[PDB]
Image (cartoon, rainbow, N blue to C red; front, side, top):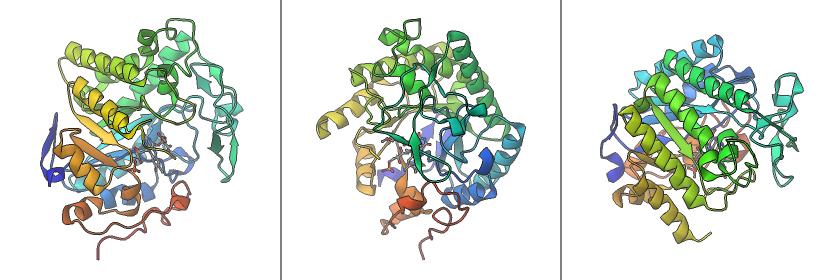
Length: 367
Ligand SMILES: Cc1cc2nc3c(=O)[nH]c(=O)nc-3n(C[C@H](O)[C@H](O)[C@H](O)COP(=O)(O)O)c2cc1C
Ligand SMILES: COCCOC(=O)/C(=N\O)C(C)=O
């Protein structure tokens, strides 16, 4: 089974290639990591396994979900430390995903009820609704398009958050540059309608992600930095006229950052276009084209099964395979995939609820 061949992710020696995908679960009450998070990641940690946390706020304006953690306060750092300690006790590697939602937010999630920030003044269309703290769905508002000064301040938020993650003991961080959130709002020409140096050409639309990655690489070192993108995704009106070219433009800039820094990033993480909340062959081809173009470790994500994961690694389509929903409902997903044991179903109704146990840590282990 190729999923259990060891793999060297730069400075981290992994014993297998089953990765816990980053997953927002909304148990971090008032944006403070809670003890429930400690039990949840502990259940899923394995010796030599790689975990990526739920997306984590880099600033008070970053959030667009209720009770998601931050890592921009010392209190948050203090509580994350306890969670990282118990994961490390199991011998796992864990990265903190740094997450800014941009225009995918709401007045209720913003300080003083201010407008969410974005590359653009265009709101997400009414085809998408935002989950509210009371469990209803609200309207995405019109965002405020930020200037280049404010852009440089968001980059500094990323840099400070990456340092706080290292202070909490994280092995590294992942830049959430995917799924129509803030970075993807700069990347996608369906969203970025800017007329300054951050829009109007493919090179300009890649500026924001390049400067974010550069800042965090300089702060904590390239081999502690992973980057997630989804050039072809149907989420929150994040379309591009040429998804493969956008992906390859990002990859080229990551390659160049690596050469200038003298070290490879931890990995590039790409979401399969089939992942939803046009050809099957052209979608597998886009993934392999990006993998072949990038000088380093490739993590694929989105709709993988045990068989699809084995095949991705055996065929050289990816080095690591991250699992989301199946990891929600199978705390010992790694052992189950090793033994080819039956997997348990997941309940989407408790994906984003606040209960510290139900649908969170009460999915059982193999008997
Ligand atoms: C409940 C839930 C929360 C998620 N939260 C995040 C997130 O915060 N950041 C992110 O990059 N991806 C997030 N994802 C996407 C996953 O990281 C992963 O790519 C996806 O679940 C893989 O597809 P799979 O569930 O079939 O394994 C989330 C997915 C789910 C189902
Ligand atoms: C169909 O693609 C959906 C991608 O969006 C996500 O998976 C996500 N965060 O990135 C959350 C919070 O669910």
